Amino acid sequence: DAPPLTLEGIKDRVLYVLKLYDKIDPEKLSVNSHFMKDLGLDSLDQVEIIMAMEDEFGFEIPDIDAEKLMCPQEIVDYIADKKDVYE
Amino acid sequence: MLKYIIPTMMLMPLTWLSKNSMIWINTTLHSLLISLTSLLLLNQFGDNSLNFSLTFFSDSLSTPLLILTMWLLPLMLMASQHHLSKENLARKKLFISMLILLQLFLIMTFTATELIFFYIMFEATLVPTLIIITRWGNQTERLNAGLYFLFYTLAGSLPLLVALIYIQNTMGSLNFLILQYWVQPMPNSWSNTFMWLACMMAFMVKMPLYGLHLWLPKAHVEAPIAGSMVLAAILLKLGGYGMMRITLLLNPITDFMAYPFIMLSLWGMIMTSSICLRQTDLKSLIAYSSVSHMALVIVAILIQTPWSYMGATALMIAHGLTSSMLFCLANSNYERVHSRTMILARGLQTLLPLMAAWWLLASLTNLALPPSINLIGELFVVMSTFSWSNITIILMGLNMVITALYSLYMLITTQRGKHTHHINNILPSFTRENALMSLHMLPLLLLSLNPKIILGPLY
Amino acid sequence: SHITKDMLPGPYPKTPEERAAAAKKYNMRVEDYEPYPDDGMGYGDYPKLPDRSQQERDPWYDWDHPDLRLNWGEPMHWDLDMYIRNRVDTSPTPVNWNLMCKHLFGFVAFMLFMFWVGETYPTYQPVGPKQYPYNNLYLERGGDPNKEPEPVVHYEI
Amino acid sequence: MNLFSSLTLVTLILLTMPIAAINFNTHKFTNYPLYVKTTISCAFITSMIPTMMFIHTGQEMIISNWHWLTIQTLKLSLSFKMDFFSMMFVPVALFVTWSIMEFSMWYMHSDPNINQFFKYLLLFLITMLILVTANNLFQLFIGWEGVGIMSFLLIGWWYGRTDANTAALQAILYNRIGDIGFILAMAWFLINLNTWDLQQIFMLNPNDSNLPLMGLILAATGKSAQFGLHPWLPSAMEGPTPVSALLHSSTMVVAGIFLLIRFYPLTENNKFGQSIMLCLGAMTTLFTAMCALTQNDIKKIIAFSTSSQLGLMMVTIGINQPHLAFLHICTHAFFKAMLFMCSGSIIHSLNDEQDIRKMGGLFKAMPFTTTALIIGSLALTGMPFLTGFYSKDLIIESANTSYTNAWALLMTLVATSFTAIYSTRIIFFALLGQPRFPTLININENNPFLINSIKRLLIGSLFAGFIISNNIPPMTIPQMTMPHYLKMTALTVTILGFILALEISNTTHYLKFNYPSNTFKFSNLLGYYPTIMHRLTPYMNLTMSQKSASSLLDLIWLETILPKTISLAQMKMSTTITSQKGLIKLYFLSFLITILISTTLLNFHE
Amino acid sequence: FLPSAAYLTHQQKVLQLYKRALRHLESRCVHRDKYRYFACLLRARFDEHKNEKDMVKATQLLREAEKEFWHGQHPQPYIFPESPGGTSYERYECYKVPEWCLDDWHPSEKAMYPDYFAKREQWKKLRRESWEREVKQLQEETPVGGPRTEALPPARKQGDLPPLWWHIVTRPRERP
Amino acid sequence: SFPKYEPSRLASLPTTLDPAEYDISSETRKAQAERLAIRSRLKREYQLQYNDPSRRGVVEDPALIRWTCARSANVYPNFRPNTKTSLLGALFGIGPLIFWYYVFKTDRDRKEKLIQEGKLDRTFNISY
Amino acid sequence: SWDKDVYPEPPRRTPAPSPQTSLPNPITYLTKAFDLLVDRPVTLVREFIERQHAKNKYYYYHREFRRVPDITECHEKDVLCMFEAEMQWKRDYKVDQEIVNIIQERLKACQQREGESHRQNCAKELQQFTQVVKAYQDRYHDLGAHYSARKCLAKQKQRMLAERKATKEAA
Amino acid sequence: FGFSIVLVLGSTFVAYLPDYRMQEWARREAERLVKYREAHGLPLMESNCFDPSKIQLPED
């Protein structure tokens, strides 16, 4: 049981599995770029995205916190709060 | 015996003519040397009891309990600081000397040939204990507790005096041997029924039985640790000792007239183990544990088997040690957090780490740990009552299940799962606390090795 | 120090007094303070609550006491000792309750009935008795050393 | 002979020194686990040799000394016997537990409270040994409650986690129900045969043997997780992994039936008792096999498997065949020790998930453990003829050829089919599926410790069943003359079970999403028994302790009847006596009527 | 029943029903791709009337949706091993020692670890430095007499740390 | 499409099919607003008395103290012995006691009669 | 040493093992190394100890007692007579319980020696067991707790009066 | 003065002491009497611990 975690590696993994999902564009997908406001995809597929991150990293995130992710940088904020991802 | 009485007299002005910050070591060292000389008593053999200084004699109903008192004194003398260190010199010395005088009337009670001398030293055991609990109770209903205490114990134990005087001037003297060797069997008219009911009702008050038991738990939970331990262990096991003595008369009627107390005792045993399943206030659970064990003891004395008497005296000694220790653990937790409730002080596996070992050990001796003396006592009581009747074993085993259940509830609720993380005043455990844990759980394991010392005179 | 008046004597009448008092003292809504009512069983003037309360109260709210499911200020439900997680799980079961106990009792009764029908109707393969030669293993049963050697032998077939 | 007694006593006493080592420690030994592993290895290699003496010639002995509390007409001493069961039982458990010492070095490497863990686990081992060597029944009671309370501490090892101490609470409660049964048995043994010493109870023939043997029945169903009292076992699986492996593979779980095998010449008689034996065993067997399907955790499935195997042992005691039941104990012990150790290795390799879903593809992810798991699941149902063959197949043969109950044999048959089908399910979903498990994968088994442990336990699970079963001293009479379709019925049922579960799997490939139809729910909701009993038997007793005990009988009515009644009577007599208005004519009229009522009415002048 | 809002909105409620049904269909359906098929079928069922604004017909459909969820839910949902009810669920809560403690040690054992205790001393000085004035004034000036929410405002005013941070910054590692 | 899920004393009714969480009135949202105000003020004073560095003892929780004084010794005032209280008292106290009295008299009379026959199985029955 | 006429050891039987093996013989190498490594040095230390015993010697005795007469030869009250009588009876009661213990130890040894064949070669010991325990059950059993000696003698009168009326009704 | 001179000395003092309640005496006395009873032909543990020649039962 030794998983190593860091900031930019998990930023890479979150950004990677957002890039792999199809109906977004890989062109204008910044690190801090929104979900609803600029990409334009709706709420329901956003919660399917949240489902993808939960199914990847091995812990549920709650519905109280599921309202407010909205961009990949804030997602990396909340996951780094979960696993305490600093040195 | 008089060489065991007279240095307890001379130990009383010790605290008086020792100066401040020097009384403590003196009282500890000298009462422990008295405990050595106490354990020197054990000369008992075979045919007779050892009888001398005509008022005095020792059975093995009296030798182990007497050693229990003369060993539980210095343990308590050490145990009762940190709650009166900040009190004054006069009340400090008065507290200590009051405990010593309490010990003196206890030993006078346990080596009583003459039963009038026994009754005088019985209520002499009563009178300082009230002053202790009422002056240093450190709660707000302690006043009502002491009042209920004295009126129950007196008014139950009062007509016992009249019945003993009636015995004294209808038969002759009250040497226990001449109570023995001369006892004529008394028939079943109604006056014999009242005399038996008088003596048995007085000690039913003292144990308590189920119907007179709210006497005790208020007096336990509203007392200092010294009065609580002496109260529980020494007073209730003194009531049992006195019943074991006085039951030698009125044999051929107590079969006919001692049914309904068995039913009250067993149903009270189940109800008491059930009422201590669901209370708060951690201090109260050990009081109701004591009521459960003493109801089982009362069943053991109403049946008249040597198996029953050996199990009775073993159950007395073991539960005296166990309940006294677990009272001391409850006091340690309450001095860590000034609460007296239970669910506030969760956690305590992490912090105070080897305190958990002593909670484990005390609670398993309450559990009937499989070589423990508690198990030996309860087992022979269950054997003897099965020979009494083949149907009583349901109540005994259901007692065993619920006893294990509340013991484990006390273990895994007070001291398991999560520190409540808003506490920040609990220290590491002092050396005195671990010293008292050691002074409780060495003699119980040594008696677990060789227990044939402390079984009854029906050996 | 603590005030005696934060305790709870008396019952709930009248409607101004105890209702305003219990709302201000138990930190609840005025009408949602519901006493028991005066069944006479003691019970004071302490509120009635919906009694299930512990495998409810969703764990992601993140209050103070992380396992007791408390909030530091609460009417502190009367039977709370009977309800802490590890004691009684009143979660909604995925089927019903009547239908649960109907299926359970039906299966237990069915197996005990077929046990009885089996008890009256044994199995046996076509098998003779175990032939024991010495008067049915006599002088190696419980005893009779020389009392009655009773002749019973087996015959070749 | 000196040699046999001296070696068995030193195999006892070499399980004493590490407790003395931590008691003389006052350090931080970083090699105390290595110490305990090597003293266990030494104890096994010194214990296998006296068993070899037993099967070479015998010299089958009891030792006893150090009497204590020889009070009335009995006496009781440290007394323990080495005979068949107590001889061949021990090295199996030593070998199993040595493997668990290895696996708990690895699996429990990264916890800084490991010394306490091995102290408790060794103390548990010593207690179970003292149970299985003793012949004085009081020492059996010692071992009974000792392994019960070590079961408590090692289930509740992970403090925190309300599941864990909940499990500990149910386990110790059902062990007290075993306790009440056992003390009823001890009571009848005392008050009708003057002792509890097993030689003497064998020496007599008790006739009215309903009550003590029913007490032993209650002891078995309270200790060894059987029906009416079984469902503490998956809750017990919600603790640590080698804890669960040791606690529910050999030790602590055969002590329900090991006692009944210890009473074999008394259970030779009293056909009513063996009828209740076999009916309870068939009930456990089919009910836990039915509950064993439709379950998504590994350890709960494997514990349901061991519960149904103990049901087969209860049926094996119901039929008069105790020694094949002992054989079932031995092969079952090696078997599930190896299976749990392999599965928990996979769990620690794949991130604490432990569930059947999200655990999909594992074959060729190094196949040492997948080899291990399928060797376990083919030793289940007895592939012919391996270590798993001997026990189960001789059980169904000797049960099929006896004066049984005509529902019990059918139940054991159907549960053999069911244990085939859930073992096929654990194979298919764990190892031979398309890979579902989350990414960032850290599959690693470059461990000398774990390959040593799995290595040597499959060694013991391929040959050693035959090493045991070959030269057993034959203590029964074999049937061996079966018809057709009664020796072939074992392989027939297992093969049809495999085909049945395979076609279940192939229809599970398809896409249909059928709604559940309540038998799915009955096999999945644990039979509704743990839910209903664990939701009702608390709430009834405590509602009958809130109103009845606390709030109504003691406090309110006892305080009304003795303090309130007397106190209010005296207070009312005070308020009528001392409430005298201060006048004088009133007091002299009292004097006057006192004079007149003393003269003419209640006379005093006579 | 949630910190910021006094209650959950209906769009929120529909969304939580969506996540629950999707999670239980994960638990229902093995092999993961027929899962993907059934999940898009479920998403199609929510696409069937997604663009209607009859709020009373919406909550009618929501009630029937709760009925059709409870009809076919799964008995043991696949919950992750850190979730409530999960396989761990604060496994190492054993090893989570609070940080108000660790200072009731002995000065020899304190002198065994020099630098961490020196930096802990300057942490504690950081705590007591800006505890009173800024934090207490921002909590007794900017809130109303009735606070009416629980999200506390940051220290945007001038300087130091946002208020009441001690037992929230100083929580343990969740895997020691 | 369901049998509409009756509750029980134990099977608690979950928050989905209430259906009281549908006909939301004015005082419902007013009650939720005031209920959040209550929880807000209590957490505010809690977090004030929880983050103080001068704080030594416990946070001195008043509601647990209040409930302890409720369950422990405020049972007896108030209490009047009514029909319900007295009848349930005389049932739960005297009833099982007199039941066990009858069963013990039954077993003891059977045993005394059987040993007065002379044929008790006292083949050896030493430890009495 | 121990008295063999009261602890009867039955005639020994030991067969000689006769291989007919070529593995050969783990137990022979085992017992050779066992004798040379265990039996010799312990015997050397024990012989050293017994020379230390034979340096100077002690004795301890059996505390023999007289026979004070009787309890049927004491009067109404006469406490100084009954004290002798009842301590004599209580010493009889202690040694009588030890007699029952010795018979039970004999029965245990008979059961273990004959192994798996219980129901032969233990007939005499079970018969004398039922005789001694029929004596004990008839004589000392149902007197309860406060045995002095007098309740035993009231039982004695009651039992022989029962058998007197039994032989009168069947005379 | 609570452990090193009290507990351990009490442990030695109750470890060995005389035959507590006359035990090993009773062992040796029972051995001598059973050797006597099985040597001299008499029945071991004769009933009627008092001789019925020394009785005067009430009659009818």
Image (cartoon, rainbow, N blue to C red):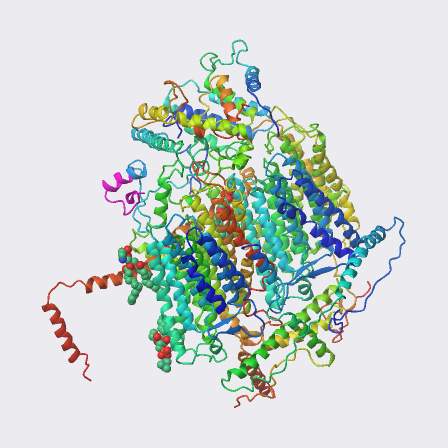
Q: Nearer the viewer, residue F94 or D13?
A: D13
Q: Which residues are magenta?
A: C1-23
Q: Position of residue F39 (x, y in %)?
A: 35, 32
User: In the displayed structure, does residue H46 sit left or right of residue G57?
Assistant: left
- Quarter of the image where the C terminus of chain D is located: bottom left
Vertical placement of residue D102 versus D179, above or below: above
User: In the displayed structure, does residue H48 sit left or right of residue F85?
Assistant: right
Which residue, as the protein is rendered here, is positioned at the far top?
A27
Q: Position of residue B280 (x, y in %)?
A: 41, 48
- Quarter of the image where the N terminus of chain D is located: bottom right
Q: Position of residue E90 (x, y in %)?
A: 52, 34
Q: Is residue D323 visible?
A: no
Vertical placement of residue E162 versus B3, above or below: above
Which corner quadrant of the image does residue A9 belong to? top right
Vertical placement of residue E93 versus E135, above or below: below
User: In the displayed structure, does residue B363 sit left or right of residue D576?
Assistant: right
Q: Nearer the viewer, residue B51 or A66?
A: B51
Q: Residue at x 24, y 45 (%)?
A: C13
